[PDB]
Amino acid sequence: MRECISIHVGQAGVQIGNACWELYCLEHGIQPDGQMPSDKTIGGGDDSFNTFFSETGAGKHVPRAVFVDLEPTVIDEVRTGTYRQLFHPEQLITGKEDAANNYARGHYTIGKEIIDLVLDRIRKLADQCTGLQGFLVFHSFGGGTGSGFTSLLMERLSVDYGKKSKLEFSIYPAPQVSTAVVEPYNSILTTHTTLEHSDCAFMVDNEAIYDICRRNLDIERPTYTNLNRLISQIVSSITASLRFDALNVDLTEFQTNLVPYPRIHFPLATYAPVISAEKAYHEQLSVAEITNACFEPANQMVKCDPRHGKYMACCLLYRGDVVPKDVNAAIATIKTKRSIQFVDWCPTGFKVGINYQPPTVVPGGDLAKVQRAVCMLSNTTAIAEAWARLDHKFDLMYAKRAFVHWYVGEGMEEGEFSEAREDMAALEKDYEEVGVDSV
Amino acid sequence: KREHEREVIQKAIEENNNFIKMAKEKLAQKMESNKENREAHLAAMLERLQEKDKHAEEVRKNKELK
Amino acid sequence: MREIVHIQAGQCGNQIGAKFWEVISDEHGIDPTGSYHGDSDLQLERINVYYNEAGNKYVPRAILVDLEPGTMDSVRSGPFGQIFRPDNFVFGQSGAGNNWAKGHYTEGAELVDSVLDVVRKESESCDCLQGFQLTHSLGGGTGSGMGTLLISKIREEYPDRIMNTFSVMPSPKVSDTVVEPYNATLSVHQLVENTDETYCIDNEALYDICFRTLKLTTPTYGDLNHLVSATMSGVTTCLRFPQLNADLRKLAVNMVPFPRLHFFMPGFAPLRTSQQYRGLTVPELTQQMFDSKNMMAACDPRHGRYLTVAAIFRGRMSMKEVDEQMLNVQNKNSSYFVEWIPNNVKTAVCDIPPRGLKMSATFIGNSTAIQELFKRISEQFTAMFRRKAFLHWYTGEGMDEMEFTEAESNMNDLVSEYQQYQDATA
Ligand SMILES: Nc1nc2c(ncn2[C@@H]2O[C@H](COP(=O)(O)OP(=O)(O)OP(=O)(O)O)[C@@H](O)[C@H]2O)c(=O)[nH]1
Ligand SMILES: Nc1nc2c(ncn2[C@@H]2O[C@H](COP(=O)(O)OP(=O)(O)O)[C@@H](O)[C@H]2O)c(=O)[nH]1
Ligand SMILES: [Mg+2]
């Protein structure tokens, strides 16, 4: 019950979804053929892992997700990858042409071709579910598939599934790994479009993840593989309440607390401890250490200063050998030392959950296995800085209407650009309003 | 009290439906506008090329005239 | 399955295109018989971008076109003349006589239709055709006039396909036809409105490089071609070997801020018997790539501003080091990069280096400086056209002086716009 269908749009979506799924197999004891020896129930069951993994007569535990990419290349490696047996052919959907980094191409010119087939596969998965809970969409703002097709699929899911949940894992563009000059355009436009169709959006800045790997993992030039593996750890901590089940707290309750107002649905995420296998050897990280780490600004997935802003919610999702008592101490300590300012309308509390299932690392990973990890999600107004930066780039190119012709030829109109930007400016003012102290 | 209870739940129903409706309409408008726009562009580029073809025919008739 | 139909027209176009095919054929392990013997799967992974498979014969998806058969006959005589599909050969007999009007209106017009037929057959075989690339010279008659004519007729058939032209800028040093300025300006005009992306291969520079750098007192056409072939290999390395700018459309999307400014300055490093074994440190290699001496186009980058730039580092090298070198050049050379275009420089590295190089650097940029080259062409045209020198040539085919005017104005307009964006700030 409470099944979740996972949707992975674009190259980034797809790859990050291959990271995640592998880690989830490793955590649940699912083998690459899908056979989970631990699971005695064959063809079905009600286990937490069944919300993300469906079962078959043979005992094979198929992932509940669909990989869509307008170029075959990325999903092709999945088709031929180690976990190719786990997935099912229909679940992998690939066209023949990419959106050449163009939102317009991916939303209209190309997307329209595959959109109906995609929704079709989702619908099949939806019928398998006894009580579907919502969708998990993974994409990148910068790419044409990750922006234009992703918004299209968001609208379609709104219509066809009504107000069912729709969470998101949006890859904030990072100049270090930038692939297109026009990525700020696609970012604004997709953010504008999906803002009304997303219940809760988690952004991950490639730059921030790139830094974390170089620093904590001592990687000279982190690859998309490094990022993805770190990303999957974050994702797994967030979804761990769903896939696993006394102290564990459903992410819904966190959601009811991380969205004070519909437009404010972007929470910041900070994970700990990211450590190399040498450094983790002969070092034990306390609940207090990992907890500090959460409040450390260099450990956050998005680059922003929480101090510059105010907290509207702050949740701590732990996993591993943790006990309430230690979590209470560490929190208090933090308090004594940190400046966790809260909006006046919001209660200055930390919602916690402890999932005793310990964390797992993919073999050959650069992440050392730890006995405890934590990932704090916070609704601080600092997130706006993000938008700003982006927006500012968008404004720079758009004043000289650069690359704008590429959008217009696909059929878009400058109105869409200006409208999208206005909405971002409103969102930024909304953050400022929520921080203002009550009269 | 019972009526108001029935009112609330019908309001929430109508709210969801209305959202689905507005969403559907908007997406249908933007798809058609874009589609028209794109075809227009293509049709104008083709017509420009055709006008260049006619100019070449005329240049060929000008040479034949002499 | 992102096929790129290739089309080589004119004397210059046929020669440079033959070289290109030989060189990529070596890089992909394909001999003149189309047989593959490469050591690396990477050569065959994207070989379909430029090659059609067949006894497993990878045939260049090329269409040769020249109004004089001699040039194409020599091509067939040359290495790999067998590899080219014989039906792809398409040559007339009249020739253009170094007349743009002859190729764009008369003799070209007679042969254009048979060319389009081969184009249509090649495009039909393409599963996902990216577009067409044309190798040609703007000074000659078949390459320019008939070239631009082919561009326009292909665009009508494939208005949704990228259109890339390696146009060769005429040079006074190279001399050759006297009315060559007219032909170049006619070609430029068509290009300005018919080509998605254009590589300004100025022969002048090529020469200069040779005489000076290559210390060649008498640069030959073979010398120039060698420079061009190495450039072309560089600018196709991302198209032919398995991210940045991997297809023609994405390159453009990221390098053409505005449709008229689709003209770019190529650049390559290192460019000389002296071996000097030291494997140019990436640092250097970067400096040379940005060096105006390594720019195939005859413009000083420091005299303008880079709208967008793209770097390719072939050869096994430290990706971290390359990254820092690029960032550094951008930082120190910040005035030479438009501020209104965030992140306008992007770079890629390929493990397989050019033949006989442990590593290379390829420079592609839409610098506003490119307006220098157009300016030289404009001066030439204005001098001749001031006296109507050789204008009767074109008028005989039915051309009118207004056409020349319009072409001159269009080229001045392109320069104006380049200078406009150069001198615009936040
Ligand atoms: N963190 C992370 N970011 C990625 C990854 N792959 C791609 N990206 C980011 O995605 C952006 C490009 O987005 P893509 O996923 O490739 O775009 P696309 O979905 O394929 O759309 P097209 O242009 O039409 O091919 C870049 O700015 C990268 O920073 C990844 O594997 N991990
Ligand atoms: N770099 C280089 N330039 C060439 C070559 N062959 C011809 N050209 C140039 O081509 C121009 C003349 O064009 P041409 O080859 O005759 O075109 P055509 O009438 O269609 O054959 C001259 O300005 C030369 O500069 C070559 O092999 N290398
Ligand atoms: Mg792609």
Image (cartoon, coloured by chain):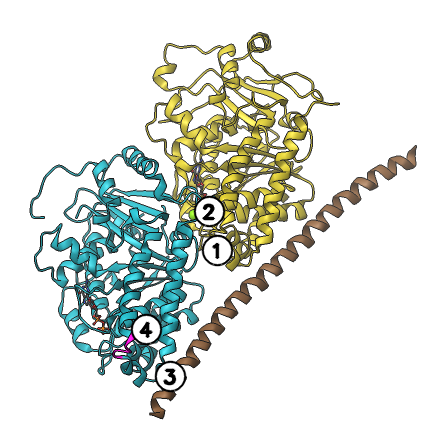
Do the residues bearing badges 2 and 1 touch, measured as CB atoms within 8 Å? Answer: yes
Q: Which chain is cyan?
A: C
Task: Using the image as rendered, state which of residue A369 and residue C392 is in the foreground.
Answer: C392
Judge depth for marks 4 and 2 and give the one in front: 2
Label 1 secondary element: helix
Q: Is residue C130 visible?
A: no
**A397 left or right of A382 in image:** left
Judge depth for marks 4 and 3 and give the one in front: 3
Specify whether disc 1 shares its chain with disc 4. Answer: no
**Disc 4 residue: CB within 8 Å of ligand 2:** no
Cα separation, mark 3 vs mark 2, equals 42 Å
Residue receiving disc 4: C118
Cα separation, mark 2 vs mark 1, equals 10 Å
Image location (x, y in percent) of residue A240:
55, 26
Residue receiving disc 2: A182
Tell me which segment is drawn in magenta. Answer: C386-390
Residue receiving disc 3: B59
Judge depth for marks 1 and 3 and give the one in front: 3
Q: Which chain is yellow?
A: A
- The question of residue C118 being in magenta is answered with no
Image location (x, y in percent) of residue C267:
25, 50
Q: Is residue A216 above or below residue A140?
A: above
**Disc 2 residue: CB within 8 Å of ligand 1:** no
Marker disc for residue A406 = 1
Label 3 secondary element: helix
Q: Amino acid at mark 3?
A: Val
Report which colour depicts chain B.
brown
Q: Is residue C322 above or below residue C207?
A: above
